[PDB]
Amino acid sequence: LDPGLQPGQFSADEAGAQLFAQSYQSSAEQVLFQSVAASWAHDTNITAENARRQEEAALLSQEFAEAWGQKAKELYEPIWQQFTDPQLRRIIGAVRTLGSANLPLAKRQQYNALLSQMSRIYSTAKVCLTCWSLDPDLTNILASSRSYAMLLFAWEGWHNAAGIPLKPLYEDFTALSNEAYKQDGFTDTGAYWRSWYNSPTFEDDLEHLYQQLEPLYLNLHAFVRRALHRRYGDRYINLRGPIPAHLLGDMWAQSWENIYDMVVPFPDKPNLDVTSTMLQQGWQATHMFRVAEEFFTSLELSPMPPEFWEGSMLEKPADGREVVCHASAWDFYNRKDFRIKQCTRVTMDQLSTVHHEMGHIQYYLQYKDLPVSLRRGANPGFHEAIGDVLALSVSTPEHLHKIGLLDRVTNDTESDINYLLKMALEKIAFLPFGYLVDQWRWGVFSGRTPPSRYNFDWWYLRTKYQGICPPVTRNETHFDAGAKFHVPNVTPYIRYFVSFVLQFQFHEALCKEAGYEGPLHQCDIYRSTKAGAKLRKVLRAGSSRPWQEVLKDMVGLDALDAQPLLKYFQLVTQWLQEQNQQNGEVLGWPEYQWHPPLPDNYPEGID
Ligand SMILES: *[C@@H]1O[C@H](CO[C@@H]2O[C@@H](C)[C@@H](O)[C@@H](O)[C@@H]2O)[C@@H](O[C@@H]2O[C@H](CO)[C@@H](O[C@H]3O[C@H](CO)[C@@H](O)[C@H](O)[C@@H]3O)[C@H](O)[C@H]2NC(C)=O)[C@H](O)[C@H]1NC(C)=O
Ligand SMILES: *[C@@H]1O[C@H](CO[C@@H]2O[C@@H](C)[C@@H](O)[C@@H](O)[C@@H]2O)[C@@H](O)[C@H](O)[C@H]1NC(C)=O
Ligand SMILES: *[C@@H]1O[C@H](CO)[C@@H](O)[C@H](O)[C@H]1NC(C)=O
Ligand SMILES: [Cl-]
Ligand SMILES: [Zn+2]
Image (tube, rainbow, N blue to C red; front, side, top):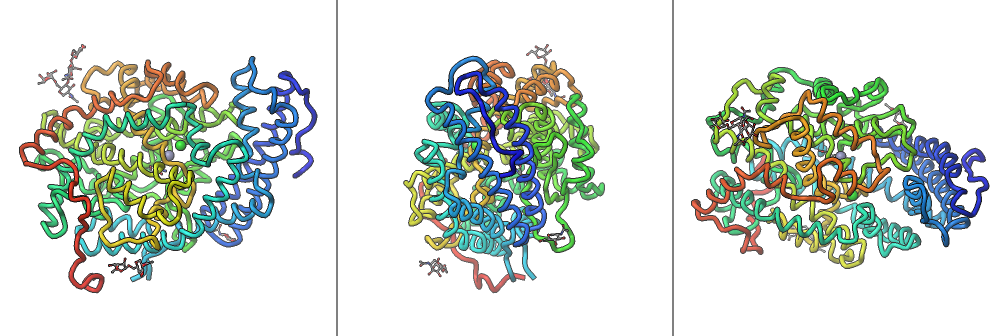
């Protein structure tokens, strides 16, 4: 570790710490920066050499964390936690969690190499027939094809190609991760990840929220299953069984907006999927990013700085470089460099993703002058909610009209149902998936789910919560959880469930602050400087204060609350319940064993 980066001397008392954190920060920014830069160089250009460089940067960060962390415990382990400065004990608390720096050097190196190899396997996996990538090729197939066999080829191909080789690496990763966090006093890595929400009742609170939301999902599920039955027929859809997992528009069946055209209740009203209009008008990634930016500046939040435009990767490279296409936002911790890395495609759903990613960047811009340990969301769910809240305004028919994407204007009950159904496909359909992923992973970290049951427990959860089934037989050689980005890329998931509840709480509060008095689902906060100021207060806080307090200031309640989501969807919630009753549906999937048959001649009968 460079002499300039090593910790010096301090008093073994409460006073010996503010100068400590200032010195830490001076060096931490340099270390964080070099780590983020090496990660960027790999993720935008996957090579063995860039993996090696990223692994060297990771070792340095671990050296740095070990040095600064052993000092805390030398000086303060018996006595720290006690009074004056709130932001200071947060900064200290973060410095003394060693994590992977607890591993001996050989295991640090193994851990870093595992992360690099898992990332490569996921982001370079292909389905061969010249071979198809996940993004754009398989993603486009899942979104647009109505060929059962083609969808199956893409789904099976992807899950086999990505999941199977990940399994042994994921096992080794899990063991090392647990070994690391156990030395910080956590029972397993999952307990560490949950500790970020600073709630002794987190898992119970989540379960109680899910109980309120589940009826909405079950009714959406039953209606969508019927719509699919009318297209695919009785061979491939069981009206009392789980929906085959490849028919819902998305590789993970995690959101269903791409099958909107099959489910739209009133097809004679204006067409709310504006993708075809975006393509007709010649939108490109650049336009999408500038349009999102202009929403942020309408609220008097910050534009994207020049360094963002110069350094970001906004389209998949056309030079045959391998890249991590999965959309992500990047803080370089130098208060200057902030970037998005997205293989942007021209679609409505991608415009929402652009807003999502830009919300992260806006957070980074607003807290860039805080101490580096405080440059985080109030919790990770807050970070995920910011862009989505703006996208809720952008997606309204009235806003789409303002930006030239929806010519017809209508305000009638049928049009409302269409809109709320489209939004339900995006937001309600996600809820079970958002909830189940870290239920799976928490069980893996705890040892409740050993390698012998990775797939059995994954599919238990997928069927339990989503009411889907794999469209081909699976066994434990398959590792279908590994075919979802966040698993091999070690990114926690519960943040997205939290976000999907939180964003409606934020939307309600911002709409009220804006002076809007109509139905919550027709609110557009565009050009509300007052809504902008309220949001800015959240963003500038970082993690300086407990999330419960930040939330209370913003929305008037100190807790996650489903009521604003329920209020937003009330009309369609009622409508779906009535339609399923009238159509004679069974809610749920009592034929829980059911899987669909294979297509004739599969896979040979596909062009
Ligand atoms: C789409 O129509 C919604 C319903 O409009 C109402 O009913 C129609 C049949 C028609 O007669 C129309 O003229 C009616 O107003 C609109 O929602 C309504 O928007 C009103 C204006 O913001 C709102 O009003 C009052 O709301 C409260 C009282 O509950 C007062 O505090 C406030 O001062 C307003 O005067 C009304 O409540 C609201 N209705 C509902 C059911 O929410 C909606 O704005 C419109 N949308 C668009 C995009 O045009
Ligand atoms: C796991 O499954 C592998 C391939 O899939 C198999 O073939 C299809 C047609 C299904 O109907 C079912 O028979 C299987 O899922 C097999 O190669 C492999 O042997 C299986 N793994 C183990 C340990 O048995
Ligand atoms: C990709 O990385 C390699 C090192 O592995 C380097 O030689 C090459 O120039 C990089 N390409 C781009 C376009 O940055
Ligand atoms: Cl999280
Ligand atoms: Zn995000």
